Image (cartoon, grey):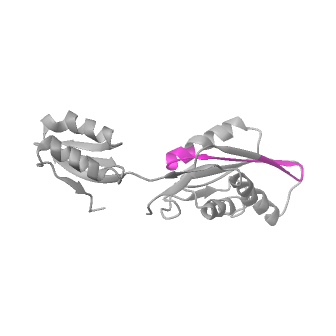
């Protein structure tokens, strides 16, 4: 992927009136697909009386990792889904999802008309989105002894590190994650803790 990226620091909600109809775009931070799906429910729930609830998202890598998605929910194919996705791709903001909510007003508009209501809707919201940088943790592996477990968890946590997954065999096989800034400080701390016999390694297979 890439070093770091920007993500949403706060949700956004904007509304608009097109030919007596009611379009309400709602943005928000969503890391991963469950997250995206998570608030589609809330926006649907919240507006049962609205005919359509079109979606789109990126689970940001940002635009490097394609955890991209969309949906028309009854609006003419390629007219309520892709348009809003291309805005999210246009923004260059990872980990975000969008929902347009349609309340039919009695007057129907063309294929163009729908595209400017959906694509455009995500466009307006995007003008009010506040962001924040996000440097993802780096992941390494580390084989230690059981009598060093608690000790290592603690050192890890002091370096803003997180123990990803454990494997309890004859020895402990740990998959750790920590800021790439703090690796050298962690290694040093680690070596002093074990008299230089612990060996932290950088993942490779994937």
Q: Is residue 17 left or right of residue 40?
A: right
Can residue 123 be seen here? The reply is: yes
Q: Is residue 137 above or below residue 156?
A: below
Residue at 68%, 64% (x, y): give it: 78
Q: Is residue 95 left or right of residue 162?
A: right
Residue at 13%, 35% (x, y): give it: 147
Q: Nearer the viewer, residue 15 or 114?
A: 15
Can residue 169 be seen here? The reply is: no
Q: Nearer the viewer, residue 127 or 107?
A: 127
| Magenta-colored stretch includes residue 61 | no
Q: Which residues are magenta?
A: 15-37
Q: Nearer the viewer, residue 173 or 37?
A: 173
Name the spot of residue 129 as percent of width and height, x first: 66, 50
| Magenta-colored stretch includes residue 23 | yes
Name the spot of residue 20 as percent of width and height, x first: 89, 49
Of the 4 image quadrants, the one containing the N terminus is bottom left
Of the 4 image quadrants, the one containing the C terminus is bottom left
Q: Is residue 60 above or below residue 147?
A: below
Residue at 68%, 56% (x, y): give it: 72
Name the spot of residue 149 as percent of width and height, x first: 19, 37
Residue at 27%, 35% (x, y): give it: 154
């Amino acid at each position: 992927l890439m070093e770091s990226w920007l993500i949403p620091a706060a949700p956004v909600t904007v509304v608009e009136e097109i030919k007596k109809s009611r379009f309400i775009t709602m943005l928000a931070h969503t890391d991963g697909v469950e997250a995206a799906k998570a608030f589609v429910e809330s926006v649907r729930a919240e507006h049962p009386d609205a005919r359509h609830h079109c979606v789109a998202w990126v689970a940001g890598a940002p635009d490097d990792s394609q955890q991209l998605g969309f949906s028309d929910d009854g609006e003419p194919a390629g007219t309520a889904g892709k348009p809003m996705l291309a805005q999210l791709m246009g923004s260059g903001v990872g980990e975000i999802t969008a929902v347009v909510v349609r309340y039919y007003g009695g007057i129907l508009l063309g294929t163009g008309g729908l595209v400017k209501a959906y694509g455009g809707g995500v466009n307006q919201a995007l003008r009010q989105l506040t962001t924040q940088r996000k440097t993802p943790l780096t992941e390494y592996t580390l084989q230690c002894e059981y009598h060093q477990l608690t000790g290592i968890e603690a050192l890890l946590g002091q370096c803003d590190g997180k123990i990803i997954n454990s494997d309890y065999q004859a020895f402990v096989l740990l998959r750790v994650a920590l800021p790439a800034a703090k690796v050298a400080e962690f290694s040093a701390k680690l070596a002093d803790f074990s008299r230089g016999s612990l060996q932290l390694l950088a993942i490779e297979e994937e």
